[PDB]
Image (spheres, grey):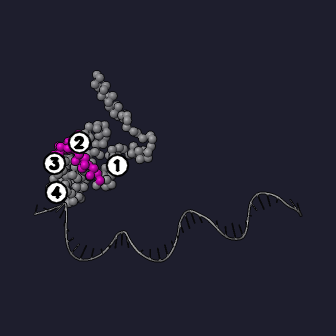
Amino acid sequence: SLLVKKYCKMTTEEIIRLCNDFELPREVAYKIVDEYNINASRLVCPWQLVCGLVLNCTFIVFNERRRKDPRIDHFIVSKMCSLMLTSKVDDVIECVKLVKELIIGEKWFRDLQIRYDDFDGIRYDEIIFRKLGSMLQTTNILVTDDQYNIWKKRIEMDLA
DNA sequence: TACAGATTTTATGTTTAGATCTTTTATGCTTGCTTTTCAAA
């Protein structure tokens, strides 16, 4: 288990290797590098911080693919347990929640949230009406128009 | 204007809501010594 190993040694090359197996953009990868570098002397297990950083960035960058396909959300963490050498998935989401405290309110995290238009899993135009307590907020008990359209196209493909 | 009746004026008592100051006690800061877990060899 890579999350158990205390005071371990790592370089930026391993960080780029982890960030290139998730196909993140390069600026986000160097911001992950800088975020590890400004905390590197004070982590009991730096792989905990790195795991939370890449998981929180890969939730944000592919928010549209996660919206149109939830199984990607069941893929990515299921892939990353293969890289942290852990069988249970609870420590990975614990890493996500523990790192989430340390980067919320940071300027680059907020700019990433703005430019991908992703604030805790939804766009601004939905979160403003859930914050206002609107009765007309787009609740999710039906399916969206894009999901309905791609499902209708897929079922018309498999009909003939 | 005459006068009964209503309202005001002046005068005081009853009860509650709150302000200020005094006395005693809690509380936090400082400084010097002692124990204890965790980062590193």
Residue B18: horizontal and vertical position, in percent?
Answer: 53, 66
Give the number of the mark in front: 4 or 1: 4
Label 3 SS = loop
**Is residue B22 rendered to the left or right of residue A114?**
right
Instruction: Report if residue A27 is visible in the image.
Output: no
**Which residue carries the number 3 mark?**
A1
Circle 4 chain: A
Label 4 SS = loop
**Which residue carries the number 1 mark?**
A114
Which mark is first along the chain, 4 or 2?
Answer: 4
Separation of disc 2 and disc 4 at Cα? 26 Å
Relative to the observer, which residue lies in front, A36 or A97?
A97
Separation of disc 2 and disc 3 at Cα? 17 Å
Give the number of the mark in front: 1 or 3: 3
Which mark is first along the chain, 4 or 3?
Answer: 3
Separation of disc 1 and disc 2 at Cα? 23 Å
User: Mark 1 and 2 residues: CB-CB less than 8 Å, in contact?
Assistant: no
